[PDB]
Amino acid sequence: GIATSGRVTNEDRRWWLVHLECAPDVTPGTFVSWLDCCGTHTTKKLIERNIWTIEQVAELDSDRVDELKYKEGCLKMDVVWEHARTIITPLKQREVSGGVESQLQSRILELRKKRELERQRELLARERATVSDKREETLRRLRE
Amino acid sequence: EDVKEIANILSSLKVRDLCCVDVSEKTSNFDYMMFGTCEGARHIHLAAWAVQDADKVHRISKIKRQQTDELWEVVPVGRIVVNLMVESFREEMTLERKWAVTRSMDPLAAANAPISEGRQVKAHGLWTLTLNLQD
Amino acid sequence: YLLDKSDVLTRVLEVVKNFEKVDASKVTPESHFVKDLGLNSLDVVEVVFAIEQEFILDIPDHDAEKIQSIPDAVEYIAQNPMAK
Amino acid sequence: NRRRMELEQQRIESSQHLPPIEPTAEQACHLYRRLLKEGYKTLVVTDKDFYRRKVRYELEVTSRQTSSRVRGIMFEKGHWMLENKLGGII
């Protein structure tokens, strides 16, 4: 993690995993700047090496990341590396499949199919309430 | 089930015009408010003290009772709140038509067509009110 | 198929007698709805719940609005094929 | 900047007719049949005879001294009662 120093325990591997709900857009094609403690500077030391996505960040051979943190002067380059090295494989299974119980596919259209039916009842409330009145008006224009 | 037992109790002590309203899911906080039209201040105290005992053996939770001041006495069963008003003091206030008219308290209540409709409000008074904006 | 007319005639000519708005001795076999029985516009359905008290089933809406001053409207009870 | 709401509100003049009709006709008699027939199924707890008296009284107190739309508001509320399956009067 960001506030973590030096080594990365086998725990905050979980903290990285638990927090993948609140990052649904993220994918192995996401820009590396989305990575815990991959700030502004370190990115520019990454882009200078043609490294852009989380996916490439998992390819570094423990020597790019080393010559990065120990020669390019980009700091915390180890706590970011272990991050892409952690979520890439649960994100790689987002390239092939989205949600498994999300979807609930027979459900997700029945939610969508009614939202048209629903948001077309207020617009029609502007109509159904008054045209029903126009008749209840014209029903009495004649009775007199 | 429990709300109907209170009616099989009060209706024995000669309470009149007893009306229950499933006020749940609506704007109020209780879920079933009932109303009773007893005549005497004593006749309001009995029905108050009588429903307490039923709230002692089946629903044992009978924390408290009050001493006096039984012109309009109120007895709650927590969320099934029973009002017991005098014969009068009902041609004044709701007895219905505030909870029998209140809409179902649903979402999307974000400043509808000017909310100053209040058929439950305009039933009793006028109550000027100005809708706001960033205006 | 339907009820015998003279049988309800023994009871419909009573239910409206001892009613709420009118005293039974202030009623006649043909006592007008508004005039002789004092009933009013809204109560045109009130006594209907005395007719629906005689014949059980629920009648379509116009029928309940159709009927005239009630002791003149039991004439439709004979016209009523739903006499239960 | 802000005055968009001015652009909005002046655009929500929206004179789709909707004046509550103020029913001065038999339309009132419709519900007073539909009510006492839709209530007669439900009045388990509350009294069946107290409930008629109040629908009467509400069909004079609202007819006697109210406005036009607020009578087309009340009458519309009569419609929305059994549409809400009742006024929660159980």
Image: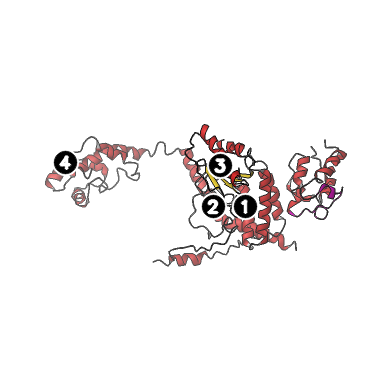
In three-dimensional space, the C-alpha distance between marks 2 and 4, rounded to whole angstroms, equals: 57 Å
Q: CA distance from mark 3 to mark 2?
A: 50 Å
Q: How is the image coloured?
A: secondary structure
Residue at image mark 3? B48
Badge 2: how crowded within 10 Å, few (<14), some, or many (20+)?
few
Q: Position of residue C35 (x, y in %)?
A: 82, 55
Residue C32: in magenta span? yes
Mark 3 residue crowding within 10 angstroms, few (<14) / some (14–19) / many (20+) = many
- Number of disc labels: 4
Label 1, secondary structure: give it.
Answer: loop
Q: Nearer the viewer, residue A37 or C56?
A: C56
User: To which chain does the residue with label 4 belong?
Assistant: A
Q: Secondary structure at mark 3?
A: helix
Q: CA distance from mark 1 to mark 2?
A: 47 Å
Q: Which residue is mark 2?
A: A120
Per the image, the residue denoted by label 4 is: A6
